[PDB]
Image (spheres, chains in turn orange, red):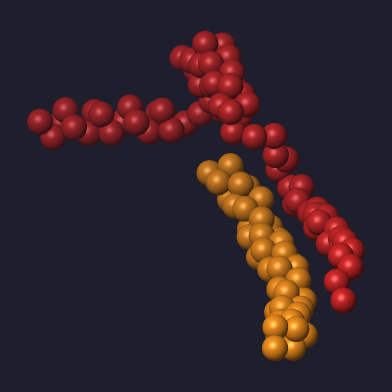
Length: 52
Length: 70
């Protein structure tokens, strides 16, 4: 009994953490694209603030 | 007091007629605000008048490791 569940324990463990590695890198590209759209507004706000 | 009032309006229009700019300032107001803005632009930032900024960024290299199980 204890070695039958030892089969099934590693097949629910592995598919959870192999999609966490999908989504831990998925957030790494959104927060570097959201900060790409935001920064290009910041360095054109400096010229909208300087000449006044 | 209206006759005193239009006497003020006369001297504002002779102050409008300018050809050399600051007549009473001289070098005192010219050396001040040129040094005042450059002391403030040093606190503001080194940005050009028409150079639009453009750049790129490098994301982290998503590496992997090994772990022998089953």
